[PDB]
Image (cartoon, coloured by chain):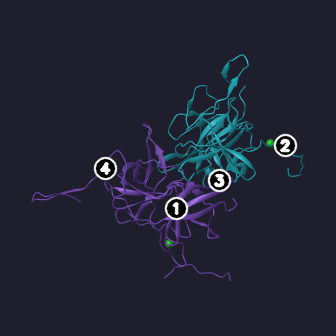
Chain colours: A cyan, B purple
Amino acid sequence: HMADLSLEKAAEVSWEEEAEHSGASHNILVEVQDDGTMKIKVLWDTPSPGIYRILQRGLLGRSQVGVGVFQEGVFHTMWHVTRGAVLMYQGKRLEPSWASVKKDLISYGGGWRFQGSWNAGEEVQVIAVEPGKNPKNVQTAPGTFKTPEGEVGAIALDFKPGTAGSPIVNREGKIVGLYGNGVVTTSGTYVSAIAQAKASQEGPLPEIEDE
Amino acid sequence: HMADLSLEKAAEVSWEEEAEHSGASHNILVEVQDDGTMKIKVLWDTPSPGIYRILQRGLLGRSQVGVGVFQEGVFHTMWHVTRGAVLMYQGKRLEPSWASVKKDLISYGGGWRFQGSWNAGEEVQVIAVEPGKNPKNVQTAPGTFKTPEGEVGAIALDFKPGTAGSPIVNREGKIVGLYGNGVVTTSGTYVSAIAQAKASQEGPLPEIEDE
Ligand SMILES: [Cl-]
Ligand SMILES: [Cl-]
Protein backbone atom coordinates (compact mmCIF):
# COMPACT_ATOMS: atom_id res chain seq x y z
CA HIS A 1 0.00 0.00 0.00
CA MET A 2 0.97 3.65 -0.43
CA ALA A 3 1.21 4.00 -4.21
CA ASP A 4 4.67 2.42 -3.88
CA LEU A 5 4.72 1.39 -7.61
CA SER A 6 5.57 3.72 -10.56
CA LEU A 7 6.22 3.33 -14.24
CA GLU A 8 8.94 4.43 -16.50
CA LYS A 9 9.09 4.08 -20.26
CA ALA A 10 11.97 2.00 -21.60
CA ALA A 11 11.27 0.95 -25.22
CA GLU A 12 8.85 0.48 -28.12
CA VAL A 13 7.49 -2.85 -29.30
CA SER A 14 8.91 -4.27 -32.60
CA TRP A 15 10.42 -7.33 -34.20
CA GLU A 16 14.14 -6.94 -34.92
CA GLU A 17 15.36 -8.61 -38.09
CA GLU A 18 18.79 -9.67 -36.86
CA ALA A 19 18.32 -9.78 -33.09
CA GLU A 20 20.40 -12.38 -31.25
CA HIS A 21 18.98 -15.95 -31.23
CA SER A 22 19.23 -17.92 -28.00
CA GLY A 23 18.28 -21.48 -27.08
CA ALA A 24 19.46 -25.09 -27.53
CA SER A 25 17.75 -25.16 -30.98
CA HIS A 26 16.16 -23.40 -33.92
CA ASN A 27 12.99 -23.92 -36.00
CA ILE A 28 13.46 -22.97 -39.63
CA LEU A 29 10.73 -23.21 -42.29
CA VAL A 30 12.15 -24.41 -45.60
CA GLU A 31 10.31 -24.19 -48.97
CA VAL A 32 11.26 -26.75 -51.54
CA GLN A 33 10.20 -26.35 -55.22
CA ASP A 34 9.77 -28.68 -58.23
CA ASP A 35 12.35 -26.53 -60.14
CA GLY A 36 15.03 -27.74 -57.65
CA THR A 37 15.21 -24.53 -55.64
CA MET A 38 15.28 -24.67 -51.86
CA LYS A 39 14.61 -21.43 -49.99
CA ILE A 40 14.55 -20.33 -46.37
CA LYS A 41 10.97 -18.93 -46.00
CA VAL A 42 -1.62 14.36 -33.58
CA LEU A 43 -0.77 13.89 -29.89
CA TRP A 44 -3.28 11.49 -28.25
CA ASP A 45 -4.37 11.99 -24.61
CA THR A 46 -3.35 8.46 -23.77
CA PRO A 47 -0.20 7.00 -22.21
CA SER A 48 2.50 6.54 -24.75
CA PRO A 49 2.45 3.05 -26.19
CA GLY A 50 5.38 0.85 -25.39
CA ILE A 51 7.29 -1.07 -22.75
CA TYR A 52 7.66 0.23 -19.20
CA ARG A 53 9.61 -0.77 -16.07
CA ILE A 54 7.58 -1.21 -12.94
CA LEU A 55 9.48 0.30 -9.98
CA GLN A 56 9.05 0.00 -6.26
CA ARG A 57 10.56 2.75 -4.11
CA GLY A 58 12.33 1.74 -0.96
CA LEU A 59 15.49 2.71 0.92
CA LEU A 60 17.86 1.72 -1.87
CA GLY A 61 16.07 3.88 -4.41
CA ARG A 62 13.74 2.44 -7.06
CA SER A 63 14.00 -1.27 -7.63
CA GLN A 64 12.46 -2.87 -10.83
CA VAL A 65 9.94 -5.51 -9.82
CA GLY A 66 8.58 -6.21 -13.41
CA VAL A 67 7.78 -4.82 -16.86
CA GLY A 68 4.51 -4.11 -18.71
CA VAL A 69 3.19 -2.75 -22.01
CA PHE A 70 0.91 0.17 -22.87
CA GLN A 71 -1.17 -0.59 -25.99
CA GLU A 72 -4.34 1.41 -26.81
CA GLY A 73 -4.40 3.10 -23.48
CA VAL A 74 -4.27 -0.11 -21.50
CA PHE A 75 -1.27 -1.23 -19.35
CA HIS A 76 -0.65 -5.02 -19.49
CA THR A 77 1.63 -6.82 -17.02
CA MET A 78 1.76 -9.98 -14.81
CA TRP A 79 -0.48 -10.65 -11.85
CA HIS A 80 2.45 -11.76 -9.68
CA VAL A 81 4.29 -8.50 -10.35
CA THR A 82 1.61 -6.15 -9.00
CA ARG A 83 -1.16 -8.24 -7.50
CA GLY A 84 -3.55 -5.44 -8.52
CA ALA A 85 -1.58 -2.58 -6.81
CA VAL A 86 -2.29 0.92 -8.06
CA LEU A 87 0.36 2.11 -10.45
CA MET A 88 1.61 5.75 -10.55
CA TYR A 89 2.21 7.23 -13.96
CA GLN A 90 2.82 11.06 -14.40
CA GLY A 91 1.35 11.63 -11.00
CA LYS A 92 -1.89 9.78 -12.04
CA ARG A 93 -3.25 6.65 -10.21
CA LEU A 94 -3.83 3.71 -12.56
CA GLU A 95 -6.34 1.25 -11.16
CA PRO A 96 -6.49 -2.39 -12.22
CA SER A 97 -9.43 -3.32 -14.50
CA TRP A 98 -9.10 -7.02 -15.29
CA ALA A 99 -6.99 -9.91 -13.96
CA SER A 100 -6.33 -13.59 -14.50
CA VAL A 101 -4.59 -15.33 -11.68
CA LYS A 102 -4.55 -18.56 -13.76
CA LYS A 103 -2.82 -17.05 -16.76
CA ASP A 104 -0.83 -14.72 -14.46
CA LEU A 105 -2.02 -11.55 -16.20
CA ILE A 106 -3.46 -8.13 -15.30
CA SER A 107 -4.61 -5.06 -17.26
CA TYR A 108 -5.11 -1.51 -16.11
CA GLY A 109 -7.47 1.06 -17.68
CA GLY A 110 -9.40 -1.46 -19.91
CA GLY A 111 -9.59 -5.09 -21.04
CA TRP A 112 -6.67 -7.07 -22.57
CA ARG A 113 -5.72 -5.54 -25.98
CA PHE A 114 -3.21 -8.01 -27.42
CA GLN A 115 -4.35 -9.86 -30.59
CA GLY A 116 -1.24 -11.98 -31.42
CA SER A 117 -1.51 -15.73 -31.27
CA TRP A 118 1.63 -17.79 -31.43
CA ASN A 119 1.76 -20.49 -34.15
CA ALA A 120 3.46 -23.76 -33.17
CA GLY A 121 6.88 -24.09 -34.82
CA GLU A 122 7.40 -20.33 -35.34
CA GLU A 123 10.26 -18.48 -33.64
CA VAL A 124 9.34 -15.46 -31.49
CA GLN A 125 11.25 -12.55 -29.92
CA VAL A 126 11.20 -11.63 -26.24
CA ILE A 127 11.79 -7.90 -25.82
CA ALA A 128 13.68 -8.45 -22.46
CA VAL A 129 13.83 -5.29 -20.40
CA GLU A 130 16.20 -6.34 -17.58
CA PRO A 131 16.76 -4.03 -14.53
CA GLY A 132 19.57 -1.52 -15.27
CA LYS A 133 20.05 -2.79 -18.89
CA ASN A 134 19.00 -1.51 -22.33
CA PRO A 135 16.05 -3.33 -23.89
CA LYS A 136 17.17 -6.30 -25.94
CA ASN A 137 15.42 -8.49 -28.51
CA VAL A 138 16.01 -12.24 -28.16
CA GLN A 139 14.85 -14.75 -30.79
CA THR A 140 13.88 -18.13 -29.57
CA ALA A 141 11.96 -21.24 -30.66
CA PRO A 142 9.26 -22.03 -28.16
CA GLY A 143 8.20 -25.59 -27.36
CA THR A 144 4.75 -26.46 -26.13
CA PHE A 145 3.62 -27.55 -22.70
CA LYS A 146 0.42 -29.54 -22.16
CA THR A 147 -2.10 -27.97 -19.74
CA PRO A 148 -5.84 -28.08 -18.96
CA GLU A 149 -7.80 -25.69 -21.30
CA GLY A 150 -5.46 -26.16 -24.32
CA GLU A 151 -1.74 -26.23 -25.15
CA VAL A 152 0.60 -23.37 -24.35
CA GLY A 153 3.85 -22.23 -25.93
CA ALA A 154 6.79 -22.39 -23.55
CA ILE A 155 10.10 -20.56 -23.77
CA ALA A 156 13.33 -21.84 -22.20
CA LEU A 157 15.21 -18.57 -21.59
CA ASP A 158 16.59 -17.15 -18.27
CA PHE A 159 16.55 -13.35 -17.68
CA LYS A 160 17.37 -11.38 -14.53
CA PRO A 161 14.75 -11.08 -11.81
CA GLY A 162 12.42 -8.16 -12.61
CA THR A 163 12.16 -9.00 -16.31
CA ALA A 164 8.69 -10.64 -15.98
CA GLY A 165 6.14 -8.82 -18.10
CA SER A 166 8.51 -8.29 -21.02
CA PRO A 167 6.46 -8.79 -24.23
CA ILE A 168 6.83 -11.67 -26.73
CA VAL A 169 6.31 -10.70 -30.39
CA ASN A 170 5.87 -12.43 -33.71
CA ARG A 171 7.40 -11.49 -37.07
CA GLU A 172 4.71 -8.78 -37.60
CA GLY A 173 5.56 -7.13 -34.28
CA LYS A 174 2.25 -8.27 -32.75
CA ILE A 175 2.37 -9.32 -29.08
CA VAL A 176 1.61 -13.04 -28.69
CA GLY A 177 2.04 -13.14 -24.87
CA LEU A 178 4.13 -11.91 -21.93
CA TYR A 179 7.18 -13.67 -20.56
CA GLY A 180 7.81 -14.56 -16.92
CA ASN A 181 5.28 -17.04 -15.60
CA GLY A 182 7.13 -20.28 -15.50
CA VAL A 183 8.16 -23.53 -13.89
CA VAL A 184 11.42 -25.39 -13.59
CA THR A 185 11.94 -28.81 -15.01
CA THR A 186 13.50 -31.70 -13.14
CA SER A 187 16.63 -31.27 -15.33
CA GLY A 188 16.87 -27.75 -13.86
CA THR A 189 15.54 -25.82 -16.91
CA TYR A 190 13.39 -22.71 -16.48
CA VAL A 191 10.49 -22.55 -18.89
CA SER A 192 8.11 -19.57 -19.16
CA ALA A 193 4.58 -19.79 -20.56
CA ILE A 194 3.71 -17.56 -23.44
CA ALA A 195 1.06 -15.93 -21.28
CA GLN A 196 -1.80 -14.57 -23.35
CA ALA A 197 -5.50 -13.75 -22.99
CA LYS A 198 -8.25 -13.12 -25.62
CA ALA A 199 -8.66 -9.44 -26.51
CA SER A 200 -11.67 -7.89 -24.69
CA GLN A 201 -14.80 -6.42 -26.36
CA GLU A 202 -17.81 -4.22 -25.62
CA GLY A 203 -20.70 -5.87 -23.74
CA PRO A 204 -24.45 -4.94 -23.79
CA LEU A 205 -25.22 -1.27 -22.93
CA PRO A 206 -26.31 -0.26 -19.36
CA GLU A 207 -27.94 3.06 -18.23
CA ILE A 208 -28.28 4.79 -14.84
CA GLU A 209 -29.23 7.64 -12.45
CA ASP A 210 -26.38 8.94 -10.29
CA GLU A 211 -25.67 12.56 -11.23
CA HIS B 1 -7.12 -12.61 -4.83
CA MET B 2 -8.41 -16.15 -4.25
CA ALA B 3 -5.85 -17.56 -1.82
CA ASP B 4 -3.63 -18.14 -4.88
CA LEU B 5 -0.43 -18.34 -2.71
CA SER B 6 0.73 -21.44 -0.73
CA LEU B 7 3.81 -22.47 1.15
CA GLU B 8 6.01 -25.44 1.04
CA LYS B 9 8.91 -26.25 3.33
CA ALA B 10 12.30 -26.56 1.66
CA ALA B 11 15.10 -26.30 4.26
CA GLU B 12 16.29 -25.37 7.76
CA VAL B 13 18.34 -22.30 8.60
CA SER B 14 22.08 -22.85 9.42
CA TRP B 15 25.57 -21.69 8.60
CA GLU B 16 27.55 -24.25 6.58
CA GLU B 17 31.23 -24.45 7.40
CA GLU B 18 32.52 -25.18 3.89
CA ALA B 19 29.73 -23.83 1.69
CA GLU B 20 30.81 -22.44 -1.67
CA HIS B 21 32.14 -18.83 -1.65
CA SER B 22 31.08 -16.56 -4.49
CA GLY B 23 31.97 -12.96 -5.38
CA ALA B 24 34.82 -10.89 -6.87
CA SER B 25 36.49 -10.81 -3.40
CA HIS B 26 36.86 -12.10 0.13
CA ASN B 27 37.16 -10.50 3.59
CA ILE B 28 39.39 -12.47 5.92
CA LEU B 29 40.15 -11.48 9.53
CA VAL B 30 43.78 -12.20 10.41
CA GLU B 31 45.17 -12.25 13.99
CA VAL B 32 48.82 -11.44 14.35
CA GLN B 33 50.69 -12.15 17.64
CA ASP B 34 53.89 -10.87 19.31
CA ASP B 35 55.21 -14.50 19.34
CA GLY B 36 55.35 -14.37 15.50
CA THR B 37 52.25 -16.47 14.90
CA MET B 38 49.72 -15.39 12.30
CA LYS B 39 46.31 -17.08 12.39
CA ILE B 40 43.14 -16.95 10.32
CA LYS B 41 40.48 -15.98 12.96
CA VAL B 42 7.69 -32.00 22.40
CA LEU B 43 5.76 -31.11 19.23
CA TRP B 44 4.80 -27.39 19.26
CA ASP B 45 1.48 -26.22 17.74
CA THR B 46 3.31 -23.77 15.53
CA PRO B 47 4.45 -23.94 11.90
CA SER B 48 7.71 -25.75 11.58
CA PRO B 49 10.62 -23.34 11.64
CA GLY B 50 12.61 -23.02 8.47
CA ILE B 51 12.68 -21.86 4.88
CA TYR B 52 9.65 -22.13 2.61
CA ARG B 53 8.89 -21.60 -1.10
CA ILE B 54 6.03 -19.29 -1.87
CA LEU B 55 3.98 -20.75 -4.76
CA GLN B 56 1.35 -19.28 -7.01
CA ARG B 57 -0.99 -21.72 -8.76
CA GLY B 58 -1.83 -21.06 -12.35
CA LEU B 59 -2.26 -23.07 -15.55
CA LEU B 60 1.32 -24.35 -15.62
CA GLY B 61 1.09 -25.73 -12.11
CA ARG B 62 2.69 -24.01 -9.11
CA SER B 63 5.25 -21.38 -9.90
CA GLN B 64 7.68 -20.12 -7.13
CA VAL B 65 7.29 -16.37 -6.73
CA GLY B 66 9.57 -16.02 -3.59
CA VAL B 67 10.85 -17.60 -0.37
CA GLY B 68 10.27 -16.84 3.33
CA VAL B 69 11.24 -18.06 6.80
CA PHE B 70 9.19 -19.34 9.75
CA GLN B 71 10.86 -18.42 13.07
CA GLU B 72 8.89 -18.46 16.36
CA GLY B 73 5.59 -18.88 14.64
CA VAL B 74 6.04 -15.89 12.39
CA PHE B 75 6.52 -16.09 8.56
CA HIS B 76 8.99 -13.48 7.22
CA THR B 77 9.28 -12.66 3.50
CA MET B 78 9.55 -9.65 1.11
CA TRP B 79 6.84 -7.10 0.53
CA HIS B 80 7.26 -7.26 -3.25
CA VAL B 81 6.76 -11.03 -3.22
CA THR B 82 3.30 -11.05 -1.62
CA ARG B 83 2.16 -7.46 -1.24
CA GLY B 84 0.24 -8.62 1.86
CA ALA B 85 -1.65 -11.51 0.10
CA VAL B 86 -3.03 -14.22 2.37
CA LEU B 87 -0.82 -17.27 2.41
CA MET B 88 -2.20 -20.85 2.57
CA TYR B 89 -0.36 -23.27 4.81
CA GLN B 90 -1.89 -26.74 5.70
CA GLY B 91 -5.25 -25.47 4.62
CA LYS B 92 -4.96 -22.50 7.09
CA ARG B 93 -5.13 -18.78 5.99
CA LEU B 94 -2.12 -16.77 7.17
CA GLU B 95 -2.87 -13.07 7.34
CA PRO B 96 -0.19 -10.39 7.18
CA SER B 97 0.59 -8.64 10.50
CA TRP B 98 3.34 -6.11 9.81
CA ALA B 99 4.95 -4.64 6.69
CA SER B 100 7.67 -2.24 5.60
CA VAL B 101 7.45 -1.08 2.04
CA LYS B 102 10.71 0.89 2.54
CA LYS B 103 12.75 -2.05 3.72
CA ASP B 104 10.75 -4.38 1.43
CA LEU B 105 9.68 -6.69 4.25
CA ILE B 106 6.51 -8.36 5.58
CA SER B 107 5.66 -10.66 8.49
CA TYR B 108 2.67 -12.88 9.03
CA GLY B 109 1.28 -14.03 12.40
CA GLY B 110 3.36 -11.56 14.56
CA GLY B 111 6.07 -8.89 14.48
CA TRP B 112 9.55 -9.35 12.92
CA ARG B 113 11.52 -11.99 14.92
CA PHE B 114 15.04 -11.81 13.47
CA GLN B 115 17.76 -10.57 15.88
CA GLY B 116 20.92 -10.83 13.68
CA SER B 117 22.76 -7.68 12.78
CA TRP B 118 25.44 -7.84 10.13
CA ASN B 119 28.89 -6.50 11.13
CA ALA B 120 30.78 -4.60 8.42
CA GLY B 121 33.66 -6.67 7.04
CA GLU B 122 32.19 -10.06 8.02
CA GLU B 123 31.27 -12.65 5.38
CA VAL B 124 27.68 -13.95 5.40
CA GLN B 125 25.84 -16.89 3.80
CA VAL B 126 22.74 -16.61 1.64
CA ILE B 127 20.64 -19.77 1.95
CA ALA B 128 19.45 -19.48 -1.75
CA VAL B 129 16.33 -21.51 -2.38
CA GLU B 130 16.01 -21.24 -6.20
CA PRO B 131 12.86 -22.56 -7.99
CA GLY B 132 13.26 -26.29 -8.80
CA LYS B 133 16.71 -26.53 -7.07
CA ASN B 134 17.93 -27.87 -3.72
CA PRO B 135 18.69 -25.21 -1.11
CA LYS B 136 22.28 -24.04 -1.31
CA ASN B 137 24.50 -22.02 1.03
CA VAL B 138 26.59 -19.30 -0.62
CA GLN B 139 29.29 -17.38 1.27
CA THR B 140 29.87 -13.85 0.24
CA ALA B 141 31.49 -10.62 1.48
CA PRO B 142 28.94 -7.84 1.50
CA GLY B 143 29.88 -4.22 0.76
CA THR B 144 27.94 -1.30 2.13
CA PHE B 145 25.63 1.10 0.36
CA LYS B 146 24.90 4.58 1.71
CA THR B 147 21.20 5.38 2.28
CA PRO B 148 19.02 7.74 4.35
CA GLU B 149 18.45 6.32 7.91
CA GLY B 150 21.88 4.59 8.16
CA GLU B 151 24.19 2.36 6.09
CA VAL B 152 23.10 -0.97 4.67
CA GLY B 153 25.04 -4.09 3.75
CA ALA B 154 24.80 -4.96 0.08
CA ILE B 155 25.45 -8.29 -1.61
CA ALA B 156 26.51 -8.64 -5.25
CA LEU B 157 25.13 -12.11 -6.10
CA ASP B 158 22.65 -13.11 -8.89
CA PHE B 159 20.12 -15.93 -8.23
CA LYS B 160 17.20 -17.10 -10.38
CA PRO B 161 13.94 -15.17 -10.27
CA GLY B 162 11.83 -16.39 -7.33
CA THR B 163 14.77 -16.57 -4.92
CA ALA B 164 13.87 -13.27 -3.14
CA GLY B 165 13.19 -13.86 0.53
CA SER B 166 16.02 -16.37 0.95
CA PRO B 167 17.61 -15.69 4.38
CA ILE B 168 21.12 -14.29 5.01
CA VAL B 169 22.91 -15.74 8.06
CA ASN B 170 25.99 -15.02 10.11
CA ARG B 171 28.51 -17.50 11.51
CA GLU B 172 26.17 -18.29 14.48
CA GLY B 173 23.32 -19.19 12.11
CA LYS B 174 21.38 -16.05 13.12
CA ILE B 175 19.45 -14.30 10.31
CA VAL B 176 20.89 -10.85 9.60
CA GLY B 177 18.47 -9.99 6.74
CA LEU B 178 16.67 -11.33 3.65
CA TYR B 179 18.07 -11.26 0.14
CA GLY B 180 16.30 -9.94 -2.95
CA ASN B 181 15.60 -6.23 -2.71
CA GLY B 182 18.15 -4.67 -4.94
CA VAL B 183 19.30 -2.24 -7.59
CA VAL B 184 21.59 -2.50 -10.57
CA THR B 185 24.71 -0.46 -10.89
CA THR B 186 25.70 1.46 -14.00
CA SER B 187 28.41 -1.20 -14.62
CA GLY B 188 25.55 -3.72 -14.83
CA THR B 189 26.02 -5.32 -11.36
CA TYR B 190 23.02 -6.47 -9.32
CA VAL B 191 23.31 -5.64 -5.64
CA SER B 192 20.77 -6.74 -3.01
CA ALA B 193 20.27 -5.00 0.33
CA ILE B 194 20.66 -7.04 3.44
CA ALA B 195 17.05 -6.29 4.30
CA GLN B 196 16.45 -6.33 8.03
CA ALA B 197 14.07 -4.83 10.60
CA LYS B 198 14.32 -4.51 14.44
CA ALA B 199 12.72 -7.43 16.29
CA SER B 200 9.23 -6.51 17.60
CA GLN B 201 8.17 -6.38 21.30
CA GLU B 202 5.07 -6.26 23.50
CA GLY B 203 3.36 -2.86 23.83
CA PRO B 204 1.19 -1.53 26.74
CA LEU B 205 -1.80 -3.77 27.68
CA PRO B 206 -5.35 -3.02 26.35
CA GLU B 207 -8.71 -4.44 27.62
CA ILE B 208 -12.20 -4.71 26.07
CA GLU B 209 -15.87 -5.80 25.91
CA ASP B 210 -16.81 -7.83 22.83
CA GLU B 211 -17.83 -11.33 23.92
CL1 LIG C 1 -13.25 -3.59 -24.15
CL1 LIG D 1 5.75 -8.88 19.50
Pick the residue in front: A147 or B45.
A147
What chain letter is assigned to the residue under label 2? A
The residues tagged by marks 2 and 1 sit, at their Cα atoms, a distance apart of 42 Å
What x and y, as percent, mark residue A132? 50, 39
Q: Are marks 2 and 3 in one subunit?
A: yes
Q: Which mark is residue B68?
A: 1
What x and y, as percent, mark residue A135? 56, 34
What x and y, as percent, mark residue A173? 68, 30
Amino acid at dot 2? Glu
What x and y, as percent, mark residue B186? 44, 37
Which residue lies most toward the top here?
Answer: A35
Query: Is ligand 1 closer than 8 angstroms to the Cβ of mark 2?
Result: yes
What residue does disc 3 label? A83
The residues tagged by marks 1 and 4 sit, at their Cα atoms, a distance apart of 27 Å
Query: Is ligand 2 closer than 8 angstroms to the Cβ of mark 4?
Result: no
What residue does disc 2 label? A202
Q: Earlier in the sequence, mark 1 or mark 4?
A: 4
Do labels 2 and 4 touch, CB within 8 Å?
Answer: no
Name the secondary structure under disc 3: loop
Query: Is ligand 2 closer than 8 angstroms to the Cβ of mark 1?
Result: no
What residue does disc 4 label? B26
Between circles 3 and 4, the one closer to the viewer is: 4
